Length: 56
Image (tube, rainbow, N blue to C red; front, side):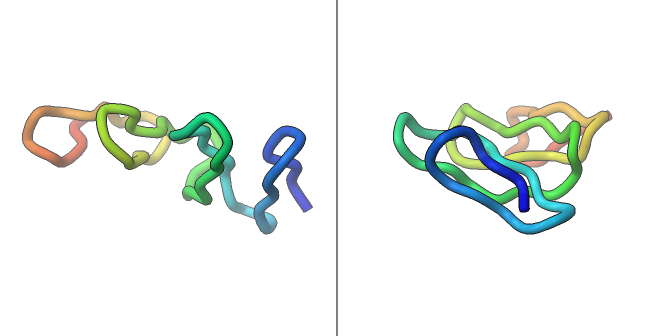
């Protein structure tokens, strides 16, 4: 599988996002961008906006 980084782990095709200090979240898209404002992530190529959603 994929080692999140000495701690958690996810399945093939998943992505490890460190939205915490000791916790890891499973997100889609390899080069995805994990929204750190709150608790989210978006497909590689998008950005987090103030509209709660992601833009391009």
